View 1 (cartoon, rainbow, N blue to C red):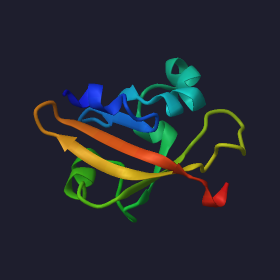
View 2: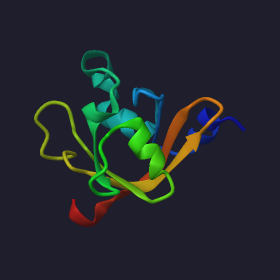
View 3: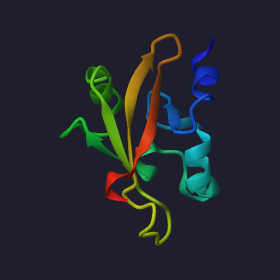
View 4: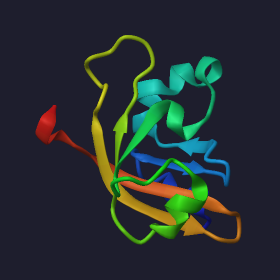
Amino acid sequence: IGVASFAKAFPWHFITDKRLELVQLGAGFMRLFGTHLATHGSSLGTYFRLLRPRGVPLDFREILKRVNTPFMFALKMPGSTALAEGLEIKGQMVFAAESDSLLFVGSPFLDGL
């Protein structure tokens, strides 16, 4: 199965290219900020803050070096939204070498909501 088709089984996923531009978003994230992609762009850092692994810049090469540890992201909601701002998503990152893609697959973490 291709990486993009695999990812579609997961509502909480994203796929980026090698510049960390989003090329696919799962249904969960599309619900939360899909409306804003046209106006706010497709840069991963526009919508996500990297929480874990700690102290890792949002840079393809640096993420790729740590691709084997668990990842956690907090959302940056467009507009004024105390509600999903800082919603946490824990999961795993996988590198697809054929296409130079990064896949994140996760699930929301409700312990601080």
